[PDB]
Image 1: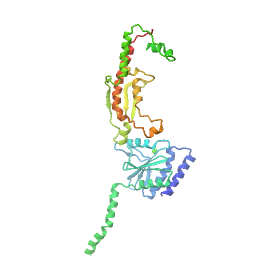
Image 2 (image 1 turned 120 degrees about the vertical axis):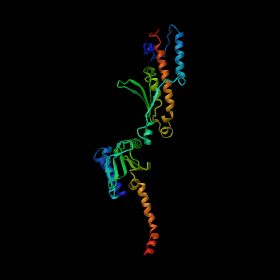
Image 3 (image 1 turned 90 degrees about the vertical axis):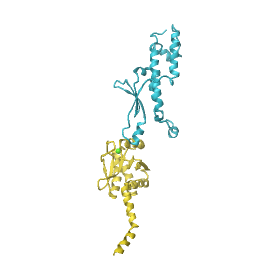
Image 4 (image 1 turned 135 degrees about the vertical axis):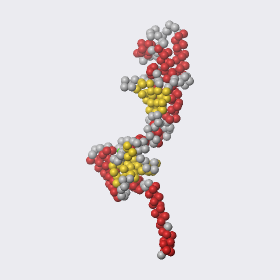
Length: 172
Length: 171
Ligand SMILES: [Ca+2]
């Protein structure tokens, strides 16, 4: 993942605008769609594209792609724009319509913004492989606080098993 | 009005020469009223305008932000004639402007359309000012504009009336 996959995306973005003669989002999205999809396959998640979600307002909204788990539970989202728009301006309108913000990569072909827990965690340039590979690591690993607390309780056992084994040995 | 119409091509190429109109008393009176309204437009009685307010689309922090952005547009009908309402921002909308108030045309724009235009959030052409010294948000000037639009509505309707009381012929 990381370098290998991101560098293939950089070449694919170039092949799309070269063999297609279009820098339109609807055509250039395939590059980041396949980055997010192939990274997910390795992390036990899948990027399912165009999945309609409902907002608090009741407005149905369809992000470009959602990161679904094995139990059909959304864990992250993605929206691509073209290079011919202001990413920051499209961001307020998107979230105003009722877009999710728990874990969303808003991305134009040149800049990528990760918004986690409602705040912009990182803003990288897609030209820098290592930088993008860093942001995508945080996106694919962001976990809800439920699993964050379970993981912490597993660590508690690693220092509680000795104390527990004493009782069982005393009983044996 | 008639002086402006008859000697129009003259006014366009020279300094405006003044006729010796018969009365004088009536003319200098009309001009004492006109100058009062125009100079002290910040003190004239606010015309009663009905302010109606609508809530943001959702409760997203961004909706409010996008709805506090200035629109300042004259709501017009399909005949492109003012319906007497102005969508100030996405939330506040003032209404009840008389049709006659759209006729104090100072230039190609009416007095009211001038107030609206010069209070819109326009990006500075200079880069340095756009980056560092661009701190005008209509939100901070909304209440002052609601007042000015009302005062200027009175200036407009009063001027149109005084100009209509003037004779229909030029010496
Ligand atoms: Ca899109």
